[PDB]
Image 1 (cartoon, chains in turn cyan, yellow):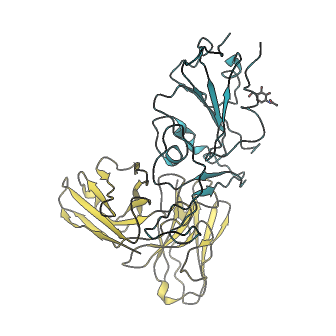
Image 2 (tube, chains in turn blue, brown; image 1 turned 180 degrees about the vertical axis):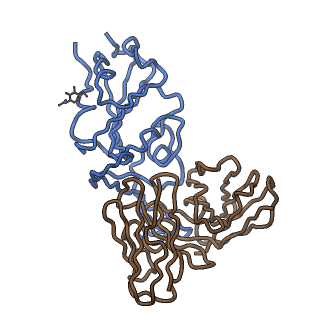
Image 3 (tube, protein in one colour; image 1 turned 60 degrees about the vertical axis):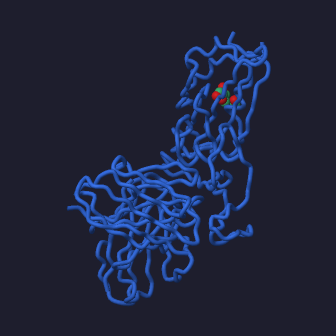
Length: 190
Length: 222
Ligand SMILES: *[C@@H]1O[C@H](CO)[C@@H](O)[C@H](O)[C@H]1NC(C)=O
C-alpha cells in the first residue's frame, strides 16, 4: 500500500564520501524489489546468502542501506572476504554477510570533494566507521599535530576528470544489508 | 633516518635464504614497507607490499616461492624464500612506501643473491655535452591520471632515489633544476644546466594503478 523508499536512495543528487558513509534504514512498509533486477543501469547487482531471484518471499525486520563513492577499480573489492586499501581501512563487510551490492557507472553526472582515508595502525571491526582527523605520528618521534616530515594527513583526495578512466571512472555503489528476525517483522514482498 | 640491510651469499637452486631490512628512526609496525628486485641489467621490479594493519600482497609473477613477514620486536622486515631458480638471481632493495605524499621516500643499501600497464621511455640514449638540456619522455600504455607517477634516478653503484613525485611535485632536497610536465598520456622530464655529476640512469614509475611497473631505463651521457 506504501512502497518502501528506494528511488531516492538509489537516485538523488548528493552522495557522501567513502570515509564517512550514511546508513539509511527502513521501518515499516512493503518493498516490491521488482525495479531492482529490472533496470539495466545496475551493472553488478551481485547478491549473497539469500537468493537473488526470489527476495519477495522473505520477511526480514530491518533493511539497511548505505551509499559510497568508489573509483571503480575497487568495486570488486567491496565483496566480503577481500583485502586491500579500502576494504581494510574504510569499510569491512562481515564474512557471513546477507544482502546485495549494486554498482553503477555514473561518470557523466559526476572533482575534489571526494576524499578517503589512507593511514591507520589497525584494521576496522565489521560495520564500523571512523570520523577522526589526527596525524598518526608515522615516525617514532612525538608529532605535535602540524604537517611535516613523518607527520602525514590521514585523509587524501581523489582526482576525478573525464578521461577514459575505465578503472578510474567515479562509481557509486550501494550495498543492502539485511538483519535477522528480532521483533515481528514489518517488511515483506507482497 | 637510515635504512640498513643484512643478508647475502651464494645459494644453489632450490635452497633457502632470508633477508633482513632493519630500520632506525622510523617505526616499521605502523608504516608501509616494500621489497623490490633489480635484475642484473634488466631494470627494476616489484615483489611485495605489507600494509600496516597486517595484510600482505605479492607480485603476480612470483608469489609461492617467497613469503614476506613483519617483525615489530626489532623494527625490521624479514623476507623468506621457499626456493631459488636460476632466473631469480638479482640484487635486492627494501624501501619505505608512501602512497601519494611521495612514493619511496627512503631506500636501503642493497644485498646480493646469486644462483649456482606498460611504460616506455622514448629518447633512449641521448648523449649530449655539458650544459645542454636533456629531455626524457615516458609514455603510458593506457590512460592514467596526472598524479600516480614518479621519477627515479640511479647513480652508478648506488641505491635509487626519487627526484619528482606525483607529476610535477618536487620533494625536499632536490634542486629546482628538475621540473616535469604532464600532458595527456605523455609525460616528460627536463634537466636544465646539465652538470657532469648527474651521469646516471633515469626511470619512470607508476603507483596505485596496479602491481607496480617500471620503465625499460635510459642512460644520460656527457
Ligand atoms: C532514478 O532511478 C529510479 C530507479 O533507479 C528511476 O525509476 C527514476 O526514473 C530515476 N529518476 C528519478 C528522477 O527518480
